Image (cartoon, rainbow, N blue to C red):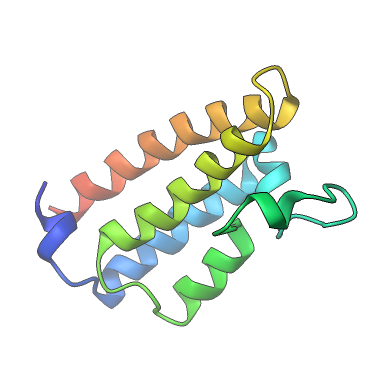
Length: 117
């Protein structure tokens, strides 16, 4: 509840983060976010989007124990959805994927915070 802000992530916590990440990676609507955006697919993306993010980058960061607090992990995840909704139009498949996957992420996140306490 404020644990998210102040309590340093533990190894036990990281098992949970990995589980959440795996659940997102397995979601059928997560397909656009699995890997970094391909420049060939979206020629102007990396000029528009200043802080790109993707689930593989986050997998790497989880592996390296990059996050010290839950808020940092959550901010990285939110960057994915925000980037998506900013770059794509509201009637795009990508945009829809962002909506679904973010609601899913919130459900899982609540799960994790509850398990944490």
